Length: 138
DNA sequence: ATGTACAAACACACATCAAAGGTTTATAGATACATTGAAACTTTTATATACGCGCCTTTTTTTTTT
Image (cartoon, rainbow, N blue to C red; front, side):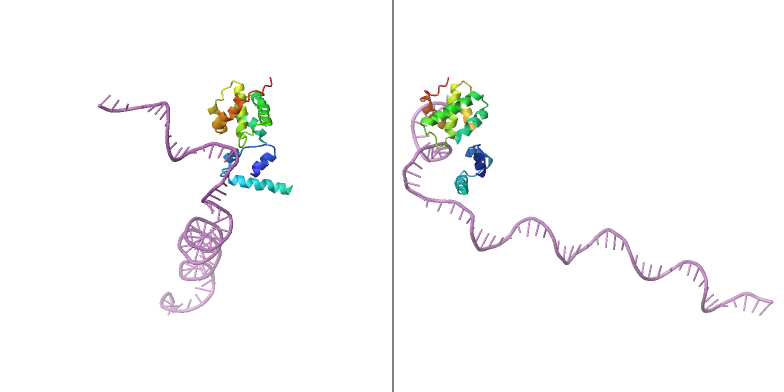
């Protein structure tokens, strides 16, 4: 966690699974340890980071990533709490925007590359195949 | 005349002393287990809250011999 602290506190945010890949922490000993730790400094006293690191993991040009910052922020800004650990609803912006482009990143390839449920995608994409109205920049 | 068994030098052949060193092993360093008690550890639950995932469980599709 002090890494996840040290990471996020250094303005680089990584998912719990990502560190879990580095160290298997039973995903639970992580959580309780984090809460105290954060409050350790508070007494001693940001999911945006995920959009680009994902695009590169798929090897995409900047525009597809460029757009998602607008889309995810705009999808976040109005409504759609949408997600229970917004890690997922980040990726759907790529999926939203990758389909706005025509580049083969077929859902199955997305999943294992980013180790995400496929179900959260399409249902997450439900709120997108309907919200396709206001993301028109050009 | 006359040299011979006998025992003293007189410098030496002979038994002794002494440094060195492999080998053995208690003896100890360090070693790897063997003990155990002790506290750091596990469990319910239900309880809604809002998740999945796999597995309970099932419906629809899928496949060899006479």
